[PDB]
Image (cartoon, rainbow, N blue to C red; front, side, top):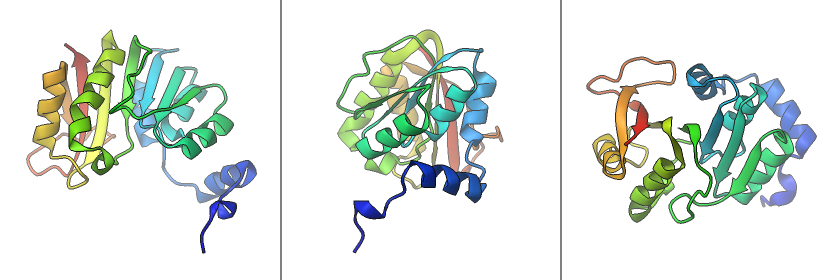
Length: 186
């Protein structure tokens, strides 16, 4: 009996998040630590803008892209000092470039079709500035085998700089169940 008249408006969203008090900004903290001040940052697969929105509040120039139009609408309401766009990274080229940082923190790789994976990563690569970095974090057993992911990344020209098993920089080791991979361009 669920329908779109059951969802939260702007007030309710804001109050419910402040009242939840959840540690939801870990990924944003890492990107902030890596960023120069006023960096240009792409939140790739941004959902309703949790990471990019936080970054916009730190004075960065943020663009968030996601395929879900309802969530981009929430982002536009919640974070009007950032820029937000509906698009599917596997099929729709990102036309903007020279991003200092690009972050993927969605952790929803299983929804990305196999044939969309290389185009998605080539897309990231093209949007990256010459001296920019891409930081992509997702879990084991959540739609993408880490070795294939790295292979696809390297094939499109994203060069692994380092890898961690968490957004708080614990080292990626044998049997690690999560990957945060940092890439440079070319």
